Image (cartoon, rainbow, N blue to C red):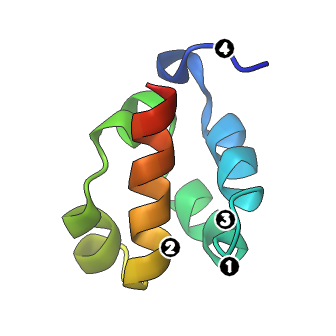
Amino acid sequence: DRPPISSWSVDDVSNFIRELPGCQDYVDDFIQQEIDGQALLRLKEKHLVNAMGMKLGPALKIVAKVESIK
């Protein structure tokens, strides 16, 4: 279904974000910031909202999904 998150490429992460409800508008940002699986595991709400300028709802959903998978 999904290989380990630590093995995900930047392209893999972009597809993951594309399929998360309400997060499709941020796909280009993840690609531009070169967020691969190892980086995704380290992303906190503060980085998403403050560093990436994301709205709180989408930011919370991303962190939560990663936590559930991990």
Asked if the residue at tag 2 contacts the one at tag 1, i.e. Cβ–Cβ closer than 8 Å, the answer is: yes
Residue type at mark 2?
Pro
Alpha carbon separation for disc pair 2 and 4:
23 Å
Disc 1 versus disc 2: nearer the observer: 2
Q: Nearer the viewer, residue 43 or 11?
A: 43
Where residue 58 is drawn, which disc sits there?
2
Q: Earlier in the sequence, mark 2 or mark 4?
A: 4
Which image quarter is the N terminus in?
top right
| Residue sitting at x 69%, y 46% | 16
Q: Residues within 10 Å of mark 2 (few under 14, many from 20)?
A: many
Residue 60, position as x, y percentages in the image = 39, 66
Q: Secondary structure at mark 2?
A: helix
Residue type at mark 4?
Pro
The residue under label 1 is: 25
Disc 2 versus disc 3: nearer the observer: 2
Asked if the residue at tag 1 contacts the one at tag 3, i.e. Cβ–Cβ closer than 8 Å, the answer is: yes
Q: Residues within 10 Å of mark 1 (few under 14, many from 20)?
A: few
Q: Earlier in the sequence, mark 4 or mark 3?
A: 4
Whether residue 56 is visible to the viewer of this picture, yes or no, is: yes
Q: Earlier in the sequence, mark 1 or mark 2?
A: 1
Q: Nearer the viewer, residue 43 or 22?
A: 22
Disc 4 versus disc 3: nearer the observer: 4
Alpha carbon separation for disc pair 4 and 3:
20 Å
Residue type at mark 3?
Val
Residue 27, position as x, y percentages in the image = 66, 65
Q: Quadrant of residue 42?
A: top left
Residue type at mark 1?
Asp
